[PDB]
Length: 435
Ligand SMILES: CCOc1ccccc1N1CCNCC1
Image (tube, rainbow, N blue to C red; front, side, top):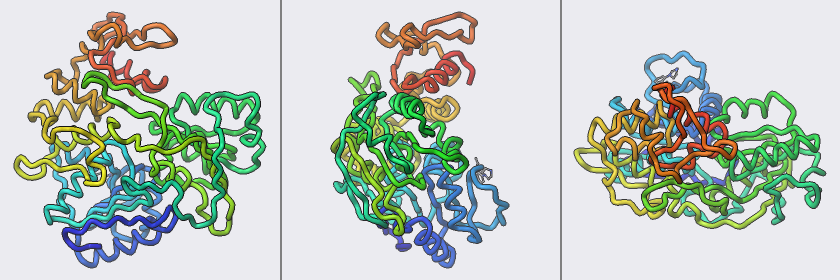
């Protein structure tokens, strides 16, 4: 696997031991061969699990998620997928790693797709090796892969709203359930219903994931209500998954605005990863997978692959060359390669809007490419009337950094800045000049 120009898809089924058994063997071999190696974890939670899998191997944990004292001599680095792409974009030295290992390599956040594009391009140039670890490579059509123990698969109507009757099977269960919902707001409504029925519920989403995931270890629970973030190596002591089989798809309309379309069907890869939360213990056969819809290839025209092109157009590779998306997922976007390349100062603005600004990639790009500087928030208030953002059925208002109360009405409207209360609070802080 470790030879130059080799990209290996380590596609063992979910729970087959890719992270805990195979990865430490790869790392031992890499160190013996003096290969400068990077290991990419999708989340801080997985970074900390990897330290346990790799204990007593000389690895530099480029994350505050791991409490370790480095020797200073490590030739293996571990960081998050997002950290890798972030450091490529910034004026910071990133080693040309001989071996590039991506764990949970199916992750479809923009920074993960961009990282696969960069790594697979360096391999194709003949510079590097890569290992992509996932049960569900891009374009997999199998929602029901093999497991450590037999799963009971049942197609059934799954509630997506509060219910009073007609779903007794949901609450009659005495075990632990992981329930995948299409959005934070949908999970809130289902969580409230379950809580009202006397169940202990933990809610997970991207922003809350590290803090709330610890509650799955520290407290007794009946249900975990999660968005698709739990597709990325989240492990639970569960015996049932309830899967809406639904997700939100960010869609760019008319090059002008981003909407959160759907909910609509998940991909096969997503469904297999959701199911893959259970069936993991060979001594516990008959974990249950209840699924409420079919799969479709909803990644086609999904904004994350356009956003991945915005990131890759702004990463130095060699002279004016630009990394291609990883071939199996390259048809998910219609972009002109290089169309999003920014000059040095606009790139710096673009990076700062994503990092400190915490804006979606697409929205950061519209602002930076318009020649607006990071702290200039005039654009948050000068959009068209249909761009008015709502809070409790009235226009959302902030006090500007000038001390003027203004309606939130961004010149470029991205539905992800107000898809839930937390997002809207963050965007209101931004529009007010508070970060
Ligand atoms: C932004 C944090 O990234 C780093 C970058 C390089 C090496 C180590 C670290 N940290 C991680 C946090 N503190 C421990 C070591």
